[PDB]
Image: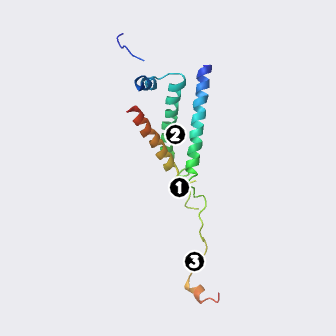
Amino acid sequence: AAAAKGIAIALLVILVICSLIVTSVILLTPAEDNSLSQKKKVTVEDLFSED
Amino acid sequence: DADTDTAARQRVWRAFENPHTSTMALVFYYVTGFFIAVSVIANVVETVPCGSSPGHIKELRYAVAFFCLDTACVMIFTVEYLLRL
């Protein structure tokens, strides 16, 4: 019981560390925000515009 | 009545085979069960729209990183299989 609870807590810690390692792995190749123009394209009208 | 179960690595891998060696076997089996559970639930949840699919990204999370979790867990599976061998 008490020893079983202690060893359960030990394995809980050694799985928490592995879960944190997994979080580090998933954040090792993150792409949260991608740089992109995300605005209007180029048409012939703006070519013939004074701009 | 005559099952005659016994108890350097020859006894070590038997102790691993033992379901309960207090400190060692409980850890060895609980952590593997956690790995298999997280693996199967990850394989399940990669289908729900909001989880990992273009089910809510058409308007604009769908982070394809559960593949890394699958790789890690199959790595655990194969290293454990090598240990069993």
Give residue A5's position: percent from left, percent from top: 61, 24
Which residue is identified by label 3?
A: A41
| Residue occupying image coordinates x 49% and y 34% | B32
Looking at the image, the residue that sits furthest to the left is: B2
Which residue is identified by label 1?
A: B55
- The amino acid type found where label 2 is placed reads Val
Look at the image and tell me in which quarter the N terminus of chain B lies.
top left
* Structural distance between the alpha carbons of marks 3 and 1: 27 Å
Report if the CB atoms under discs 2 and 3 are less than 8 Å apart.
no
| Residue occupying image coordinates x 56% and y 45% | A22
User: Which of pointers 1 and 2 lies earlier in the amino acid sequence?
Assistant: 2
Element class at badge 3: loop
Give residue A38's position: percent from left, percent from top: 60, 70
The chain letter under disc 2 is B
Give residue B24's position: percent from left, percent from top: 52, 26
| Residue occupying image coordinates x 50% and y 30% | B28
Report if the CB atoms under discs 1 and 2 are less than 8 Å apart.
no
Give residue B75's position: percent from left, percent from top: 45, 42
Element class at badge 1: loop
Q: Which mark is residue B17?
A: none
Element class at badge 2: helix
Which residue is identified by label 2?
A: B38
- The amino acid type found where label 3 is placed reads Lys
* Structural distance between the alpha carbons of marks 2 and 3: 45 Å
- The amino acid type found where label 1 is placed reads Gly
Asked whether B23 or B12 is in front, the reply is B12
